[PDB]
Amino acid sequence: MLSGLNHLTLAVSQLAPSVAFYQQLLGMTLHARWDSGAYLSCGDLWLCLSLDPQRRVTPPEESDYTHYAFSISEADFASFAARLEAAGVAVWKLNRSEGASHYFLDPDGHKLELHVGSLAQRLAACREQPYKGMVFFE
Amino acid sequence: MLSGLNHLTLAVSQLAPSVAFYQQLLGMTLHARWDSGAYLSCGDLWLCLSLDPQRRVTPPEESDYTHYAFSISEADFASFAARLEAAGVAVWKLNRSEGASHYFLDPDGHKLELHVGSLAQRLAACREQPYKGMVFF
Ligand SMILES: O=C(N/N=C/c1cccs1)C1CC1
Ligand SMILES: O=C(N/N=C/c1cccs1)C1CC1
Ligand SMILES: [Mn+2]
Ligand SMILES: [Mn+2]
């Protein structure tokens, strides 16, 4: 039986800018680095950066909607978004759903998000206003 | 301050086969589905499958090493991997370069993994068998 997300691995084209982004800009803890990657943590998340010459710096119009959202409190959201803005980090989408969300790109174009709110919160909102074709499972 | 992964969203080309994969084959919990997506959980993980006309069914030699690993116990690992194999699930990697792992593909070619062990355990294993040039902080 699967018990959760064990780790997220992102392929990166250049290790040093990716470490700078995740450790210094985003505040994740760097536990180890080697010639072709790094291990960080973000709360319970184990993140691996893997240096990969196949990684392309990918514009957001060229990738699909697959994306990775990090948790932040409502109280901290606006100042963290402003930090990303000051750093010139590109936005790939505006928020139109429930709960605060800031949609930003990593140095290789990985699609990231800051989001406030849980799955339970989303399901409660959806129960009140279901999406087209929505059905729930108890 | 960031505190972990809020959710993983995977773009999918065909919603129903993807839901079936994650719910029926991988055993994740399906909470809701709608015309353009589904919400599942795997322990505390919130997984969203999002129907996306832009998603390509992608062979593993065409995509980079980005991948998503799910936790499984030592006792369950081998029989779960063998069941995925017997069900015809495609693979993408054989060499266990990061401990006890099984590397497999979802219907759209998303790179998945079964892994036994935490980050702390991986760091301890690496102190004995480090990756080339490894430094620990
Ligand atoms: O809300 C979350 N997970 N929820 C998991 C669930 C498992 C079973 C029901 S809800 C993540 C913090 C964002
Ligand atoms: O699962 C079912 N219904 N669930 C309804 C729910 C409404 C709101 C949350 S669950 C039916 C037996 C097939
Ligand atoms: Mn999202
Ligand atoms: Mn892995």
Image (cartoon, coloured by chain):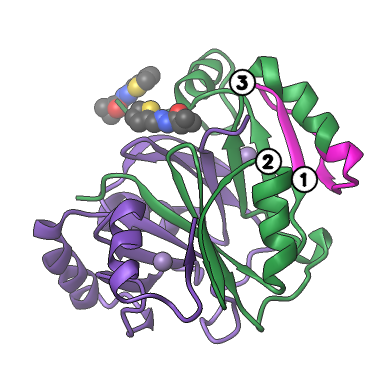
Chain colours: A green, B purple
State left or right for residue A102 relative to residue B55: right
User: Residue A57's mark?
Assistant: none
- Residues drawn in magenta: A84-103
Visible residue check, residue B106: no
- Furthest-left residue in view? B75
Q: Taking B26 as reference, is A108 above or below it?
A: below
Q: Amino acid at mark 1?
A: Phe
Query: Both on one chain, marks 1 and 3?
Result: yes
Query: Mark 2 and 1 residues: CB-CB less than 8 Å, in contact?
Result: yes
User: Residue A73's mark?
Assistant: 3
Q: Nearer the viewer, residue B76 or A76?
A: A76
**Element marked by disc 3:** loop
State left or right for residue A107 relative to residue B51: right
Chain designation of label 2: A
Residue in the picture at 42% in, 39% down: A44
Quarter of image, ligand 2: top left
State left or right for residue B44 relative to residue B100: right
* Rendered location of residue B18, percent (x, y): 44, 57
Q: Amino acid at mark 2?
A: Glu
- Whether the magenta-drawn stretch holds residue A99 is answered as yes
User: Residue A104's mark?
Assistant: 1
**Element marked by disc 2:** strand
Q: Which residue is mark 2?
A: A113
- Whether the magenta-drawn stretch holds residue A80 is answered as no
Query: Mark 2 and 3 residues: CB-CB less than 8 Å, in contact?
Result: no
* Rendered location of residue A37, percent (x, y): 55, 70
* Rendered location of residue B72, percent (x, y): 23, 54
Image quadrant occupied by the C terminus of chain A:
top left
